[PDB]
Image 1: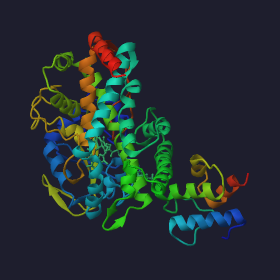
Image 2: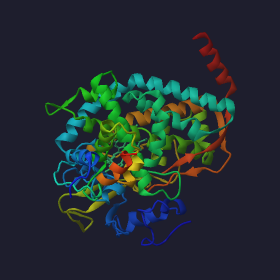
Image 3: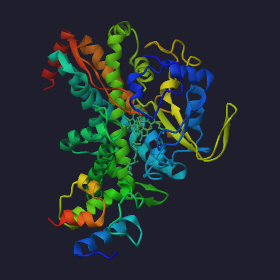
Image 4: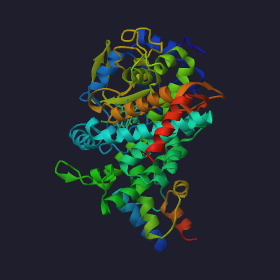
Length: 417
Length: 75
Ligand code: HEM
Ligand SMILES: *P(=O)(O)OCC(C)(C)[C@@H](O)C(=O)NCCC(=O)NCCSC(=O)c1c[nH]cn1
């Protein structure tokens, strides 16, 4: 279903993204009102909506006239702030942000993540071969859910036995699997993550290991150690940040490939590089639909004045379908070059796990093209509900295995045993 | 208003240290006093360790006040 009017669409409601195809809505905003004022809804204030790639890029870059210290997603921005402001990386600006990012780059740089990449490739291969042997599986639960969380947990130093518990909590923090989730259940889930990590951080400061929590606990910003509170809040943003979005991208690729069998064949038959295909998967899926800022000073854009205190939302989903930047934007094209998508954001807050997210998708696509000849959707897919995230929580598939490649994989493991 | 037993008195003292303020009402709601997640985390984990009680987070949310928590603890 396609809406022609702009005023009817309420972007704060998660139901909006289920019942409607907003492709026409975003096009209309992009061409006729690039800076649109979304009206107040209930107790929530109004907010600016930015839809053009160029404007989205320009506002991500400006950390001087815009700030993240009042929140960076709708739920925090419309509440008037984020409790973790100035402590959690994503909601910190200025010197504290630069220092805190610099200590995290010791762990999340391409240079530091290389040994981890090997583990991602091994785990992903193993899971894909399992699913291919069975034939009939649920790609979300049996493959996708078992990679991103496990990766970030290994880095953080989360005990294996607590990981299933953490996945349940993540699935309630910013998005629900059920239609009408109250703010209570989400609050409980978010704080349960905080309660878990305050126990684990206390354990790691008392007895340090070599994981990221230990690296943070022994790091310094501005000549002073990080408080346990600051470490816990960042752990929250890593466990949830390194989980949902990657997971959704991986699920979306499998669904998209069934819709675009010509592009699956290009990947299967080695007619496109994994690097090129990973970028189109990321442009297509855009699992984080929006991020946001708040104006600290007055600014003019397209003749309209954005006042100090105004909530400004940047829509990555709209930016990745801009005709001015992407030729045939609603075409899924693995050969797309250049592919300067804004899925990982831009500027000072550019995704800290961009390399890690890319490595996870890359490993999946490599495993799918090697040990699979094709796949098909068998049941009704299940959409997550959110004004922030987009994707599926469940995807029933039948996988046709590449039997020769699986036999070679088994023979290889036989002599390595 | 003053705390009416050892449990209420001990709990109010925890509220004060967590919220960084004196004059904490024993009957007032935690969230109406500007209480957030960071403070809630420290609060619950401190109540658990000092009262040797496995207080669920849901129980804290349903009765986020000194008086209510004291009733739930004493049982
Ligand atoms: C493909 C999946 C991913 C997507 C779509 C994505 C998206 C984004 C975006 C758009 C931002 C910018 C936020 C802003 O400007 O306010 C961001 C930042 C961030 N991301 Fe991701 N991300 C992904 C994977 C990951 C992974 C694997 C991690 C684990 C390390 C992670 C952790 C973070 C953190 C900690 C920030 C805050 C950076 C800062 O404030 O400087 N993300 N992400
Ligand atoms: P309480 O007072 O309710 O506060 C909880 C908490 C301290 C966690 C607070 O910061 C909050 O409410 N945050 C909102 C949830 C949130 O913003 N999570 C991070 C979004 S996922 C994300 O940014 C990302 C980036 N890359 C991948 N994923």
